[PDB]
Length: 49
Length: 49
Image (tube, rainbow over all chains, first blue to last red; front, side, top):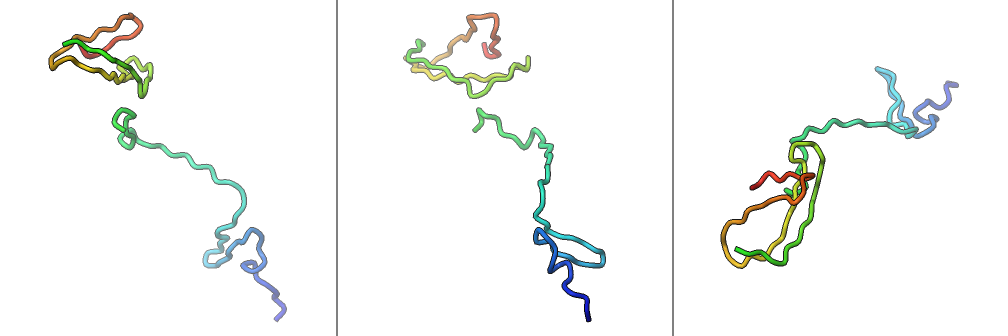
């Protein structure tokens, strides 16, 4: 009766909270580095453009 | 054949030691035929004769 608000309602950064498993989703905090290894076949030669 | 009004541009160049550069040369030919191609410097080797 006295639980109060759940984390999906109180969490910072707009976090969505779910269980089974316990998850914090889509928290808009920080940066995410991405490294992509692109095969030579994916590129078009300058002279062919 | 005699060529006039020639101009040269190089869309890309890499000194890869494997013909990594490509030159595009615009020309106005007096008539249809074949022309020899030669580099005037030892610094640059051209694959097409």
